Amino acid sequence: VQLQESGGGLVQPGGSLRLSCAASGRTISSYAMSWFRQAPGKEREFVATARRSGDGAFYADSVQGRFTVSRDNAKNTVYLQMNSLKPEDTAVYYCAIDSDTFYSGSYDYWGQGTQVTVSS
Amino acid sequence: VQLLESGGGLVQPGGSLRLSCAAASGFTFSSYDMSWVRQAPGKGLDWVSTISGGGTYTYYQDSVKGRFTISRDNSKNTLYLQMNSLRAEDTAVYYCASMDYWGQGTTVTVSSASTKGPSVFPLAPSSKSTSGGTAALGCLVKDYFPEPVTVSWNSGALTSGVHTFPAVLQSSGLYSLSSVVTVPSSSLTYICNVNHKPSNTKVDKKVEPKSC
Amino acid sequence: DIQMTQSPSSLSASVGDRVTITCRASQSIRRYLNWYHQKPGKAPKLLIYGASTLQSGVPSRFSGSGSGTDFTLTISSLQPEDFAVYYCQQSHSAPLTFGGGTKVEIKRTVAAPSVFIFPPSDEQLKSGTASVVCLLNNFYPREAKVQWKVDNALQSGNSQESVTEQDSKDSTYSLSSTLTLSKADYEKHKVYACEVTHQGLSSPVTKSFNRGEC
Image 1 (tube, chains in turn brown, cyan, yellow):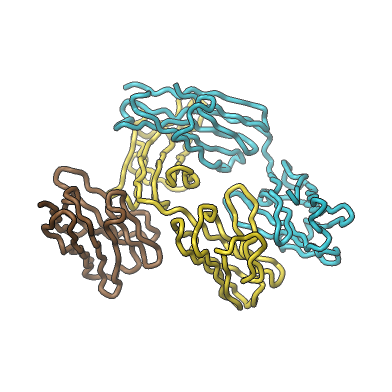
Image 2 (image 1 turned 60 degrees about the vertical axis):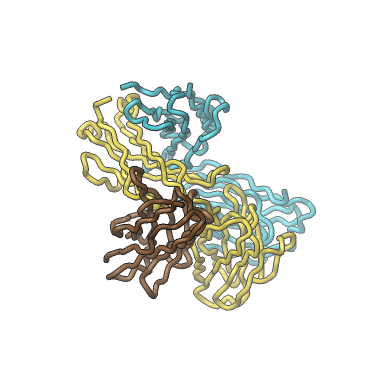
């Protein structure tokens, strides 16, 4: 299994971006998928998680109300819809599988990251 | 309060207890099929026994059949449960219940342990172990019987950030729990007040950070 | 017996949500099914009998449906009093049996645990036993994993874990893991480590101390 984030880019404050994390290989529908972000010279931080369908979506304080995480099992893909972008949202954005079916956060598999930059 | 249980408490394996349940006057106790249902610590609801309203028919869960006897006295609005040959697994809160109303239950604790107050040990932070703005400290409340203990901090002045965990039954037959609190690192007095009413014992333990 | 199975074990919801809970019986019970509500430390309260009939005084946002073997409890607009454990119960035949429960808990934002590790006290050590405590504080959601490593050897069978109810103010959980050894075993080893994972953590958090050092 491999992951590839795409949809990063440059956007003005208040604008939107739609991130996608595609998983090549084994089927991920039974595992939670999580988004993290890492700004330059700051720790890697939690953004969102989409658990199995029906098990709910969970968000960090910083992105609550603005970002929506969702999944397409048919496409082995997870999406992060980012609305009302802020300059502080600038970071590289990563997705990861939780290899634990019971959701304890065993992030073994990571994608390479997509750059998000919000600026005038 | 429409139903009130009594007759529970401490017993040893192989012993007997008689539970009784008194209904308030306007409850129409005579019209109800009446039941005992039990709940073990950390577990769900477990049906014990039912008796019909006029007393003709009694029904039992298999694991209490022949050990427990349900009965009722409609003139006194009272339900009984005679429990013989008790075992440790019978330890639970026992509720007196009609379909639409449950009493608050009575605790039965079946154990070989003797009543014993707790030992209290500090959970101390240190200079090495404390990084950032928040420190944690607490008290390990160990080897007591039966439940419960209450834990307060600085005689009840410190409440914000306090977490007292539910007790665990150890293989010794004695209970254990911790109580913790987080405070500013720069604040590093903190004393946990441990009360164990069944033994009439009380222990105050000052929790001291160590310096490295 | 008639096995009652409930789904999901737990669900996270907010005030105003529409919540559905399901109950399935091994046999057909056709409508002899009750739903109960229980807050920690309190007796259960009947919400629905005959699997659709609202019980007197229960607010109308509660409804039940179903017959045969599949039953549903719906709360149309969740209120703060509704965060509780819900049980189904068949009244069809003896033995009377309950479902295993569904906890309806308060949803909030993700908080990774802060981890703290405490050595045994010198007073306890003299007694012959060592309790090493690891605290996971103020985290959400509930799922977490805590492992013990003593001189890097993963421990099994010598720890107990305990968890608080959702905090009344911030809706987080806290959890303790207690590792218990004999004095003689404890004094063999140098490094005592607590390793923690949570969906809010990008990599596992380890807290440790060296026995015999400050």
